[PDB]
Amino acid sequence: SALTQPPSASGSLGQSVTISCTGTSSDVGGYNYVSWEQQHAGKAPKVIIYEVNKRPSGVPDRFSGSKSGNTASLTVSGLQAEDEADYYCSSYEGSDNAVEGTGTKVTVL
Amino acid sequence: SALTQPPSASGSLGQSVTISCTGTSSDVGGYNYVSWEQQHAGKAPKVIIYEVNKRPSGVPDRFSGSKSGNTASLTVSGLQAEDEADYYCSSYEGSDNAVEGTGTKVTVL
Amino acid sequence: ALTQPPSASGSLGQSVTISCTGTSSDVGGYNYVSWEQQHAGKAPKVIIYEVNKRPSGVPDRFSGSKSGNTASLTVSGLQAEDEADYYCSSYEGSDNAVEGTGTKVTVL
Amino acid sequence: SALTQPPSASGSLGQSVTISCTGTSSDVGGYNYVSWEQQHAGKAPKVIIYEVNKRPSGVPDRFSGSKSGNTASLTVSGLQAEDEADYYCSSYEGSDNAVEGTGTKVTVL
Amino acid sequence: SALTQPPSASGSLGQSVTISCTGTSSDVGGYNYVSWEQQHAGKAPKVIIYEVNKRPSGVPDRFSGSKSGNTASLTVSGLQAEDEADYYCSSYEGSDNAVEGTGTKVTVL
Amino acid sequence: SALTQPPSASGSLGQSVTISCTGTSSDVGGYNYVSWEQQHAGKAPKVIIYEVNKRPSGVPDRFSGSKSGNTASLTVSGLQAEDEADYYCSSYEGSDNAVEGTGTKVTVL
Amino acid sequence: SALTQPPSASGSLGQSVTISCTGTSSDVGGYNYVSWEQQHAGKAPKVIIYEVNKRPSGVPDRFSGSKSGNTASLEDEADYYCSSYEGSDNAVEGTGTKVTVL
Amino acid sequence: SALTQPPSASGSLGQSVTISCTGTSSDVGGYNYVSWEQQHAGKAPKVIIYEVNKRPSGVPDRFSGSKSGNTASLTVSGLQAEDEADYYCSSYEGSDNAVEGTGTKVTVL
């Protein structure tokens, strides 16, 4: 199930940090529906990237995302104090989304 | 993982047979995407009902389908020889369709 | 195919009504029935779409409706230019699926 | 109407078998929604591949699928005894979504 | 405004004929929803191509379609007797599909 | 082809104003896609209602919309200074969205 | 903007707790796509309810969810966040340009 | 959150003016659904371009639109007196379609 991220990363004020998020062909490699959430300690998460590289309203362009193959990336440039937080990526996950019946043999007499 | 059907059913030529297909709120009770396939021995299945009660082109009106709650039904009236076969129901199955990352603590130095 | 009577008639000034029977997959399933009017060896012209809506420049004496699996066109104040073939059409639903003939795999 | 598959195929224990599934631009050549089902005699089919090359949970990686143009392929490697079965491919089919009336000649008297 | 077609075309039994259908960026050049209907004299039309190059069930592959820019084409090869008919192309036509209100000046006291 | 609105309306601070928007079965009476935009003099419009009665983020619940038959309504309660503006309704408009070719008579041999 | 939840709630071992989640017709009142996530401190969230009242595999039945109007309701010491599908006008407007001629 | 346009632009009678409209990958760079409205002082807006470069009926070809990357453009050539007006661009905006709760800390006694 889970998408692999490094547990720690760092950068300096004004600089850039990049964090990665590895999954499989069922999610990150399969679809363009990767998101990144930013969460301060004991606060609710905020979406900062959806659909791989698209920013919600009021999220600045210094946050950006991309992917290649099964690895997605978030990059934060012009790093600021408010950017210290946990960052979780998420993705659409595939499933055949189908359940099959056991079958009924109909005989005609 | 499966929709419950009786394994046997019968009817006579010219008569009706009805066969049931029980699932849950995740599939039959949750959506209007139940299908029925008809399959002759060592032959490929053919869809006879989709979206609960809709017939593909070239499937006659004596085949019909419905559902209530978690149980869907196929009815075959004016039963004919070609109707002796196995009959499998299927349905869309729900799933949260989402996978979560392990998280990265970003520190700003 | 949607069932229509092949012939119908009316007198000048009068009305004619023609029917169009389908199934729950089309006429009984959706509100997307159209009627086209076509003169011999001429291109069809849409006269009704979405069951009862007229395109621009089509007069109100053409009108349409449906009930259950049967849709209807009515032409009132019948005129000479109204002699033509009239075809109904409808959105058709689809399972959107095609099945293969199968292969028996043997393990030797 | 139907997707073309060879009716027989074979392989030896431990080896590979590959089976093909030819359609048109309306299905296999048009979309990435080709599935393969595996079915044992008088048993219900099980989905083994969906969306061309994606495996449901609990289906091993030795089953794999692909396509090129109008032909899709299932490959089974490390062939085992339980793999003797019928295998059916299926695909999303596009549709003009339109049905035409037979016409009425209106005469004005 | 109508789509331009030559009023006549011809071919010999066994040979090919190709017929063109010119529109604008609002229809043929704007979308992939061009159709071709075949119609015998005083008979109802039958769809033979939809969505530019896709064939309905039971329509053979010797009918084919394509487009480039604002011109779409139907090609019939292996010409047969039953292929003598009128052939009409059609397309989705764009429109902003929006109607505007005249506006209300709201004053607050 | 315009939706009818009264050109003027008024209310006092703290009070309510309601403004109407009449169309036809082709738009307001035909679909649930009516919008209302608010526009200050020589400023760009802002959407305040879409899909008849749904508010975008950051638009308060004192703006509300509804419709009955061919008439849609916007209501502003707890009227405030910033609410003095022009208000335009808009709607999805239907059209058969289809264009027909002139036809080609194909002769064989 | 955000769905309203009480910031604290309390229950005793063996007992029940219920927590609420108020939104609008654009989300909780508009659709059946409300979720609840459970999150331990500095750990990743886990979905415990989706589509209002449906439990993922391996989540026990003692967790349950429901909604009425705009209000949805739902180691166990943790933070619990609800979320929902949000509808959208799906449109953005330009600031405008006054065009002058000559 | 808004699309950037210059507030003023000018041209001479008979000449051309071009005005730009910069957004992001969520709208102008993401989709082909950019529109331009023309609005005279205290009059209702009129759509002059939709779907990037398509003109509604009765709008002449001297109005034209295009885009490259995140910038869309309207060009008016053969400039006339009636063309003095405000001009607003708009675009489909993508959306994560998700709203997050503020969170509840549950404590157990």
Image (spheres, coloured by chain):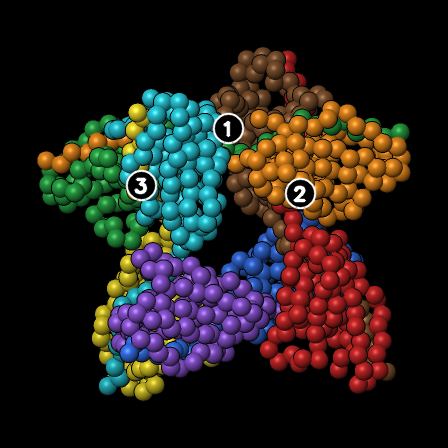
Chain colours: A blue, B purple, C cyan, D yellow, E green, F orange, G red, H brown
Q: Is residue A26 above or below residue C83?
A: below
- Does D76 sit left or right of A45 as displayed? left
Residue C5: give its label: 3
Residue type marked 1:
Arg
The reply to whether residue E100 is visible in this rendering is yes
The image quadrant of residue G64 is: bottom right
Q: Separation of disc 1 and disc 2 at Cα?
A: 27 Å
Residue D92: give x, y in percent of width and height.
39, 59
The reply to whether residue E28 is visible in this rendering is no
Q: Is residue G75 above or below residue H80?
A: below
Residue C5: give x, y in percent of width and height.
31, 41
Q: Identify which residue is drawn at 73% across, 62% down.
A: G68
Q: Which residue is mark 1?
A: H55
Query: Badge 3: few (under 14), some or many (20 or more) residues near its Cα, within 10 Å?
Result: some
Residue E48: give its label: none
Residue E76: give x, y in percent of width and height.
20, 42
Q: Separation of disc 2 and disc 3 at Cα?
A: 42 Å
- Does D6 sit left or right of G63 as displayed? left
